Image 1: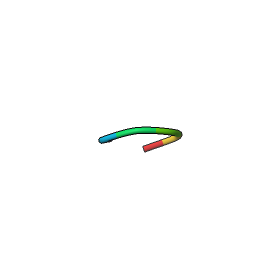
Image 2: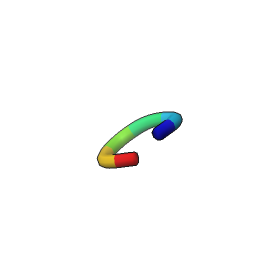
Image 3: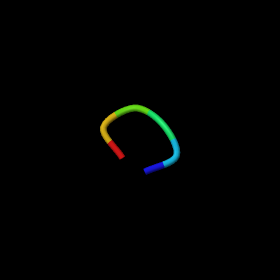
Image 4: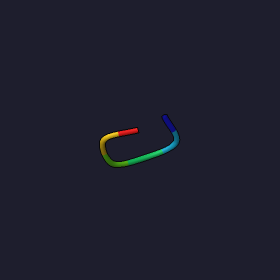
Length: 6
């Protein structure tokens, strides 16, 4: 969500 895959 916040960064990367999330």
